Image (cartoon, rainbow, N blue to C red):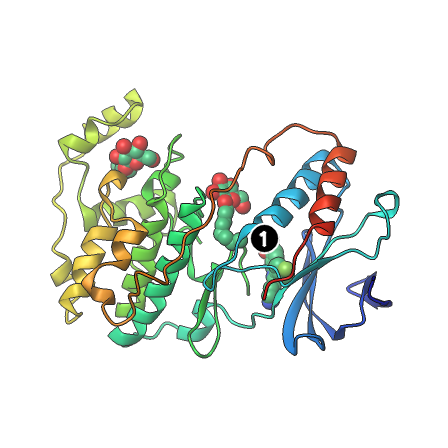
Amino acid sequence: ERPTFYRQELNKTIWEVPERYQNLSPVGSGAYGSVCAAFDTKTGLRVAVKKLSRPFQSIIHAKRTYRELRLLKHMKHENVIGLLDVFTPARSLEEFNDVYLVTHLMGADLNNIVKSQKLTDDHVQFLIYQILRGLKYIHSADIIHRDLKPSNLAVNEDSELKILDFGLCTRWYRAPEIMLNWMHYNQTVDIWSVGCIMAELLTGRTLFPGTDHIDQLKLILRLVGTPGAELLKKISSESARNYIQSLTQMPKMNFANVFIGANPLAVDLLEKMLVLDSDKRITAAQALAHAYFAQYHDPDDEPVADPYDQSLESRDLLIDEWKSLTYDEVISFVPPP
Ligand SMILES: C[S@](=O)c1ccc(-c2nc(-c3ccc(F)cc3)c(-c3ccncc3)[nH]2)cc1
Ligand SMILES: CCCCCCCCO[C@@H]1O[C@H](CO)[C@@H](O)[C@H](O)[C@H]1O
Ligand SMILES: CCCCCCCCO[C@@H]1O[C@H](CO)[C@@H](O)[C@H](O)[C@H]1O
């Protein structure tokens, strides 16, 4: 049984949606497509509905539409954006051209909730605990976020937090190896970001507000020191090793004299997150077991994902192949409990 759809002009196109979604009100448009807030009469929930723009305009658009859908369908965790619904007005493949995605309405990001204020230690424990819990899940699926920052973090007024992959509402939270276009990366690029987020929550200041790419690097090296010999050993590029070999060696500052007054557990966790050598950074699961999170840690409700086959989305296919693939993802969607 199909729901009854209704047609309505919004953000300069005809939106066509099930009647369960009421009171459509645009929150944003862009090249990606646009979004309305709505009330979902069926669940009683305030929801965001995204209408993809030009989803099947080209191979690249089609490919991306398929990845976005597939990723959304696989993310099922309290601290990660998930899918409430996916729908198309289309009744067959032959007429399939629009894709709408539904999730909880999110009216505020982490910036919007903290507003450059120091938070209490307890409040930072809660926020960070959740980021890390979502990241354990995400990383267990063999995914690296790669651009974790306060704008990619949805936080309601109960400080309940979800990781996003789009700015809801800088380069300051990026791992130094991402800033340096390092060919390889591990999941601890995201742990670096968490450390930057956590420092700023504690202190009320951006940790490394560089004015540009190199000023950013200088600020980082100042806190965490220049590469040691173990780290230099693992540099492939002759130009990167010759650059480093020519730096005046600086020592890693004492984080106790940077985070004056902070809980000593908080300083300890930060020392473990903000190691230059990414092989040396704490992992999410490890950070979740750290004493800093004693009050929130439950080793039995820190769930993992089935690894996520990213090969199916990096194929080189034809428009109408990606579109039928995407159409099957729509048809197969099972609403969550
Ligand atoms: C690339 S651009 O900066 C961009 C901006 C916003 C969004 C954007 N996408 C969504 C959104 C909506 C429904 C979904 F199912 C998935 C994502 C939202 C959203 C979700 C919940 N409440 C408010 C807004 N914002 C996507 C891309
Ligand atoms: C759905 C929210 C879960 C977070 C998973 C985010 C996965 C993001 O994955 C990232 O996407 C970028 C392009 O936007 C790529 O350039 C990066 O290489 C990639 O790591
Ligand atoms: C001058 C500033 C240099 C920044 C040093 C970045 C060190 C990051 O750490 C490196 O991460 C790589 C993945 O990117 C791994 O392959 C390396 O083994 C690891 O040491």
Residue behind label 1 places its C-beta within 8 angstroms of ligand 1: yes
Viewer-proximal residue among 300 and 106: 300
| Above or below, comparing residue 333 to residue 202 in the picture | above
> Is 78 placed above or below 274 here?
below
Task: Decide if residue 129 is in sight here.
Answer: yes
Name the side, left or right, on which 228 lies relative to 321.
Answer: left
Residue 188 in which image quadrant: top left
In the image, taking residue 220 as reference, residue 17 lies left or right, namely right
Image location of residue 152, percent across then percent down: 48, 59
How many numbered discs, if any?
A: 1
Residue drawn 47% across the image and 64% down it: 78
Query: Residue lying furthest top in this view?
Result: 238
Q: Secondary structure at mark 1?
A: helix
Residue in the picture at 43% in, 44% down? 144
Nearer-the-camera pick, 121 or 289: 289
The answer to which quarter of the image holds residue 333 is bottom right
Instruction: Measuring from the top left, give residue 206's x and y in whole percent.
Output: 32, 62
Q: Which residue is mark 1?
A: 72
Name the residue rendered at 78%, 55% in the picture. Answer: 88
Q: Which residue is located at x 83 percent, y 57 percent?
A: 89
Q: Is 64 on the left or on the right of 132, as rendered? A: right
Q: Could you tell me residue 35's position as x and y percent?
A: 68, 63
The one nearer the camera, 330 or 238, is 330
Q: Quadrant of ligand 3?
A: top left
Viewer-proximal residue, 10 or 309?
309
Q: Position of residue 204 (x, y in %)?
A: 30, 70
**Three-letter residue code for mark 1:** Leu
Q: Is residue 329 left or right of residue 142?
A: right
In this rendering, the answer to whether 186 lies above or below 169 is above
Q: Quadrant of the C terminus?
A: bottom right
